[PDB]
Image (cartoon, rainbow, N blue to C red; front, side):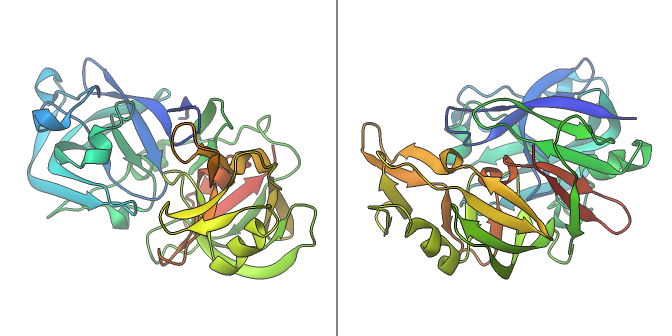
Length: 330
């Protein structure tokens, strides 16, 4: 089997991407944030505290003839941005782009933090990291990809995120029309539960490539590119007026600037992020200070190849017995 679904930016900055997902019988379609940095499929629901729902579409398990309470199971998750959610668990039929999994754990939110309530466009998350990170207790549950894998034509999914435009998540096949050149594959460590890999270096603009190993995660659920402070300083030093602002929470730059590109290495190959992809717009409405799309990872503990980096590439998440990551230009 295969599936193919379009993923759409939630706003004009590509702050996140939503993909329609069918849950239950008859189908209830929710728009979920596919997140290769986590491993829980959770949704706003008929059980979510009413004051914490503000415009999201909800899953109502009592209206699904295939929903079954997973008795005793609870979940609770906290994300790197400080947001969180928790609740109980049903199993139900879940389909993405024509690919159907029966018995998928659907984690129903009883509580969500303010940032989820405040984002009316995201109805939940669909985790695509390794199932060892799934938070369901006392019986850990499998991701949608893990459950689908055996049925797929090939044990892979691909992320093809657009810049200010829709893109595609494919399951079970590699669309050879969706990229240019060849795909360069690189090793993955699953020891932390992430799609963790080592970039071979970077360049700023037209500058020379610096060969240096940068360990990080491929994370579709993170907006920006978080890299070591040395790398980030070298980038922003090429932008007149750019500075790190403790009050804003990162590097800012004059909105009048033209940003240089940023290149990262994948083996001997190179992915170029155009400068425009690094512009996240005014820090507040009407400001002439703009927020940078490359930020320091120094306070995180891990480097994160988020959407800013991933949307410059066609990315293969290869879930074979030894997982690997593939990157192609497009």
